[PDB]
Amino acid sequence: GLTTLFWLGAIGMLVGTLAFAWAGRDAGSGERRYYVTLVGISGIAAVAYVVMALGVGWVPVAERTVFAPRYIDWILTTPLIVYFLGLLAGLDSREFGIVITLNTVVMLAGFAGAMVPGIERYALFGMGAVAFLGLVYYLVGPMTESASQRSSGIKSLYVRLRNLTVILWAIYPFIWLLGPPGVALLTPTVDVALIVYLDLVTKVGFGFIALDAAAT
Amino acid sequence: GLTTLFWLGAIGMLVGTLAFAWAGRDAGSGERRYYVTLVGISGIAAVAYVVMALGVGWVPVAERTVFAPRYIDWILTTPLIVYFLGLLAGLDSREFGIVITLNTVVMLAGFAGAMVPGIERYALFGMGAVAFLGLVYYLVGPMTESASQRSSGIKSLYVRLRNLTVILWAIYPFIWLLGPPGVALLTPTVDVALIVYLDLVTKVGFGFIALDAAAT
Amino acid sequence: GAVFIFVGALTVLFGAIAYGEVTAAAATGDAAAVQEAAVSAILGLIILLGINLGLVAATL
Amino acid sequence: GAVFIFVGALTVLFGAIAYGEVTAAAATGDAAAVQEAAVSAILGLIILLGINLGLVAATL
Ligand SMILES: *C/C=C(C)/C=C/C=C(C)/C=C/C1=C(C)CCCC1(C)C
Ligand SMILES: *C/C=C(C)/C=C/C=C(C)/C=C/C1=C(C)CCCC1(C)C
Image (cartoon, rainbow over all chains, first blue to last red; front, side):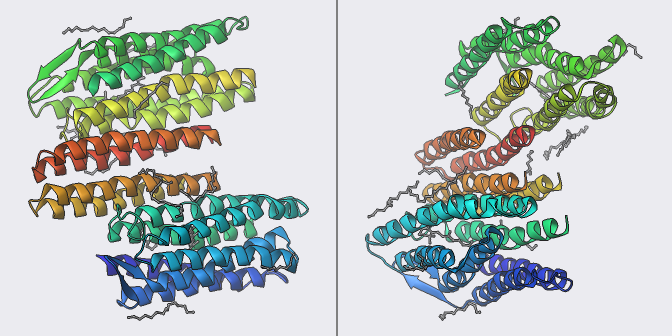
């Protein structure tokens, strides 16, 4: 059942949210921004999953069904994930506006493409993909260089979080292609299940690994 | 095609065999026994896969087909794998005859059970499983204690090889239960494919990890 | 080590969801409907390996 | 790192074998035959995760 999967998403995101608010209660002098950000990432996502679980935002497009809340989520949370990674890396402002802009282009292209019945949706996907490679270049390149200047515990947490992000974000566009927006080889249910799993790892899992290391 | 999968098994085992004979050419004063053993493990298996690929040893049993060579392989090679692990661990002779006997009981029980149409094949499986837990206890217990006394490079290679063995050998009895000998939920082709993959990792993969560490 | 048991638990959950689609398709009596459900399940499970590896890799 | 690409390569090979069974079943026109082929493919792929994890774990 689709709404059952959405409800499991909501509950997972909530647990994560409550966990980050709680853990954050005793955050250091310049660590609050991390905890605030994670409550933002998982809290926004929880609300989105609730909305989908209630049946709202299910858009008909040709022969598929596009979940608008999913994409509105991504546009808001994925740059917050990138902001988090920018914090460990130690970016200045200029470096932020590049990657965040790249990231935003990806989600808008996926969203746009998702909403287009015609074959030109693949061109839109094309542009999202090119922007993604741009984002990846920044994560593994310059931002990694930046992160090398920091204390080794922070570097190691960066590499760990960058690896989780780059690997798992690279899976999304495949779900897009094989799923309803692309060739429709994955049923809506399987598409939703995979994303729910991804969203929980990329946000809640991402977060807990950070809780683990902020202690250790 | 079944025989195609067997032929891929044979070729994989052969490559491994040639690799171990070659690498062994420049083995140390007390390292030859390791290389000899790996040529034994992968060479016996190669011959078995060739035999199956040629269509020989396909035994009719009730509504399934049991590959006798597969099991004759296991009876010969699995104790050789255990002998290898006994070498890194530094066992004396008494400790060898326990684990090898345990191991032998597992394969005979699987083989016997495989050849029995009746429901009592699960009792035979039962006994194989109990012996396996016995073997596992020795790998993670006493043999691990033994291996701790050795130089750290050997200890680390032991843990690495013990982990690969315990984890992957634990998968076999599930293939037995879900496959043709058990509930027949896995088609013969899928059963053969999974085992081919396992046999290559547990032997050739096992071996290469040892080549990697005997250098490093 | 506990990560695997989490991964394994979810992987069988996902299998059960996919399987549940296959069987519903089967009760339809239409082989094409079962095949469409089967391809989705195979591709999903392949994709699911990649997620688990990423989660394992990142944690290992 | 190369291990993953080896694992991924094999995992898609296995998918293609399983899929090839599903389709052969499909050409039969019998939904039950497709379902029997689908369950085998799902269980195989689940089992295949465990093998890949073991190989990853042992190597990580
Ligand atoms: C918590 C939710 C997350 C981390 C969502 C990440 C989504 C992506 C990385 C989507 C990437 C896409 C492309 C790279 C291509 C165009 C299709 C997209 C938007 C799905
Ligand atoms: C290279 C070939 C190898 C490492 C084969 C290993 C086979 C096993 C560990 C089989 C175990 C079984 C049980 C534990 C239960 C009874 C069924 C068996 C024999 C399949």
